Amino acid sequence: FMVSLPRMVYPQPKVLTPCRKDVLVVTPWLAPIVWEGTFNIDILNEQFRLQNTTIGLTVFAIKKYVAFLKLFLETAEKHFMVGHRVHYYVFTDQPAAVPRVTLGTGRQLSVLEVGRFLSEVDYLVCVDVDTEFRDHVGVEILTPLFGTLHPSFYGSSREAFTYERRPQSQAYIPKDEGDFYYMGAFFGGSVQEVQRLTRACHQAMMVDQANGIEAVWHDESHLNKYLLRHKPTKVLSPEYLWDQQLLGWPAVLRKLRFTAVP
Ligand SMILES: O=c1ccn([C@@H]2O[C@H](COP(=O)(O)OP(=O)(O)O)[C@@H](O)[C@H]2O)c(=O)[nH]1
Ligand SMILES: [Hg+2]
Ligand SMILES: [Hg+2]
Ligand SMILES: [Hg+2]
Ligand SMILES: [Hg+2]
Ligand SMILES: [Hg+2]
Ligand SMILES: [Mn+2]
């Protein structure tokens, strides 16, 4: 059940003015593509806060990657879901190497040692740890299932996408299929949908391994197969995982929100 929004004062949406004339802002299956200029964050914050939304943010930090956790968490504190309930889950082989990072109110961190989500959070966001937040990443992303446009491929034709191309792999996508090339480094959704996805990818990877084949881009290849056959209900623009060193700051990006660390 959803309670009413309060009175709010904001600019009227303009039916005869496009949000953007330079980019696609809705997919052919009517999922929004999230770019700066498309959303009013005050409206969305109200909607999600009224639901007391809790967001889980999951990161793996194994071996040398524990080195990335301090900048990742400190910047998440500044930029990720500020105002909302956040639960970070850090999966690591080195629990004692996790940095002591000061968290805002309503935000918590669990360290899980590696060799429940359903009761604790509403959405799960799964990201690589060698990254840092530089600008707002908020409730605009939340939806049952989302993927993010890979920054090297957002302007490419589908034939250039580096999908798995061998028919022998569960991850196979032929040259005449494919909407986008999604990044393995940043996807999420409701807990139920993320667990569906990871279960499907895990089963497909086991089949591939039993068959002697490893997809060309591993988890990312399988994510792209899944999102081909189960269309995401939002797609994030490359604002959401950019690489400024590799790719600069092109005019189509009004904000650089979350970026690879060198
Ligand atoms: O030795 C490793 C290798 C990778 N990872 C995790 O797996 C992700 C994927 O590897 P990485 O991001 O370095 O590869 P990329 O695709 O960015 O080059 C990393 O961000 C970490 O979250 C890790 O924890 N330890
Ligand atoms: Hg707009
Ligand atoms: Hg995850
Ligand atoms: Hg999959
Ligand atoms: Hg997998
Ligand atoms: Hg996957
Ligand atoms: Mn990475």
Image (cartoon, rainbow, N blue to C red):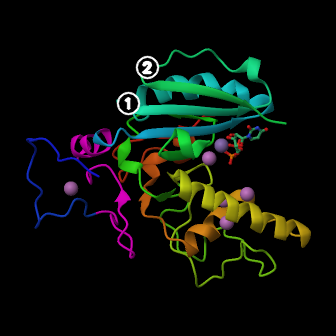
Residue 7 visible, this angle? yes
**Mark 2–mark 1 contact, CB under 8 Å?**
yes
Q: Secondary structure at mark 1?
A: loop
225 shown above or below 52: below
Q: Nearer the viewer, residue 181 or 152?
A: 181
Rendered image: mark on residue 104: 2
Whole-Å distance between the Cαs marked 2 and 1? 8 Å
Determine crowd level at label 1: few under 14, some 14-19, many 20+ residues with C-alpha closer than 10 A.
some
Residue 188 image offset from top left, x and y in percent: 53, 51
Provide the major secondary structure of the magenta segment.
Answer: loop
Find residue 165 and report its image quarter: bottom right
Amino acid at the residue labelled 2 = Gly
Ligand 1 positioned in quadrant: top right
Q: Nearer the viewer, residue 124 or 59?
A: 124
User: Is 97 left or right of 74, judged from the image as shown?
Assistant: right
Q: Secondary structure at mark 2?
A: loop
Amino acid at the residue labelled 1 = Val
Residue 69 image offset from top left, x and y in percent: 64, 26
Q: Which residues are magenta?
A: 22-49
127 shown above or below 167: above
Q: Return the residue at label 1.
A: 82
Instruction: Tell me which numbered mark, 2 or 1, is placed earlier along the sequence.
Output: 1
101 shown above or below 165: above
Residue 183 visible, this angle? no
Residue 209 forms part of the magenta stretch? no
Residue 12 image offset from top left, x and y in percent: 8, 53
Residue 47 forms part of the magenta stretch? yes
Residue 159 image offset from top left, x and y in percent: 60, 77
Q: Residue at x 39, y 75 (%)?
A: 29
Which quarter of the rendered picture does the C terminus lie within?
Answer: top right
